[PDB]
Image (cartoon, helix red, strand yellow):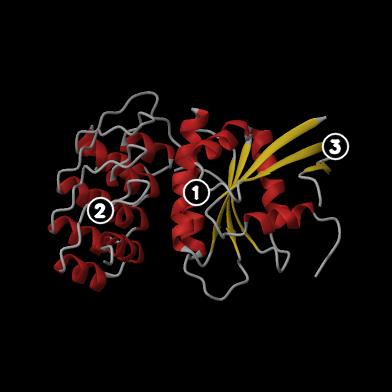
Amino acid sequence: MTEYKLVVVGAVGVGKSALTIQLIQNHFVDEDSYRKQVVIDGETCLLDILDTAGQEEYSAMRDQYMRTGEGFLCVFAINNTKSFEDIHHYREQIKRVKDSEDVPMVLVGNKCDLPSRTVDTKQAQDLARSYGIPFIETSAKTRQGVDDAFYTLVREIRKH
Amino acid sequence: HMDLGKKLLEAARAGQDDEVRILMANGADVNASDRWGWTPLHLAAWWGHLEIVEVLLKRGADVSAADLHGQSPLHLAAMVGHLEIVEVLLKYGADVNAKDTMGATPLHLAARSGHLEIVEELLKNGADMNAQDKFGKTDLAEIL
């Protein structure tokens, strides 16, 4: 069966783990596996997910995730301007590690339910257009965009 | 013991003209860089703060500063689509054909990002172009 190796990247505190947990969970709660079997567009496939949380600062290991990953969920938080510009650094590093300008990626604006917004939707849409990638706003807390983000990344890998 | 370079980088990111000028009046290093090699001019160029770009350039910002990925402020403005900033950087002597560590010129990045007017502005300033500078989803008389 087809496997999709997905890597979740982004600055410390942008909600990488919360997003991943929200995708993987099979029931609501107010232990699980990051190899999740799903059916996408009629075909049974495996999502093989790697979260960089805990190793964002660890250069040698960041590069190891980038080597193995087939597609990248590039997560920033909409109330953290530094995390948004960090996407540029992650994208440039992915290009260099993989020696390619055409790596599957999706830009994810997380915590979209919070009122303290410092990155405008327009800025993020424009950046995604320049990068040639989809942009999705997400919130694990309000269950918005999470399925769409991961589904869209799989579609980007399939198109490559 | 406050790091004025760090504060200047933060002010440039935020587009805070007051803070930028106050910090530079206090001697803050205009070419201070972060862990990735981004200077205040890199930040102003990427974020699209035209006023801040002009202020930094007037006070001796190095237009040629290259980050850890070999990118100059011109690479950043060209990729993200900030035409007025591209123009000002070229006016202040930016190297139009500077290559980053992937071998990319600012034109290579602008072309891939679909910024035709920027590609043309770079060509007007002597940019090299070749068949590998492919276009993404998108005067002329002067260039031709």
- In depth, the one of B141 and A136 nearer the eye is A136
Residue at 84% over, 36% down: A43
Mark 1 residue element: helix
Mark 2 — on which chain does it sit?
Answer: B
The image shows residue A17, relative to residue A143, as above or below, that is above
Question: What residue did someone put label 2 on?
Answer: B32
Q: Are marks 2 and 1 on the same chain?
A: no
In depth, the one of B29 and A153 nearer the eye is B29
Mark 3 residue element: strand
Tell whether B106 sits left or right of A74: left
Image location (x, y in percent) of residue A156? 64, 39
Asked if badges 1 and 3 are on one and the same chain, I answer yes
**Viewed as shown, does residue A127 lie left or right of B43?**
right
> Rounded to the nearest whole Å, what is the CA distance between mark 2 and mark 1?
30 Å
Within 10 Å of the Cα at label 1, are there few (<14), some (14-19), or many (20+) other Cα atoms?
some
| Mark 2 or mark 3, whichever is nearer to me | 2
Residue B142's spot in the image, x, y percent? 19, 38
Characterize the local packing of mark 3: few (<14), some (14-19) or many (20 or more) Cα atoms within 10 angstroms.
few
Q: Earlier in the sequence, mark 1 or mark 3?
A: 3
Callout 1: chain: A
Amino acid, disc 3: Thr
Q: Which numbered dot is residue A129? A: 1
Residue at 69% across, 34% down:
A158
Residue type indicated by callout 1: Arg
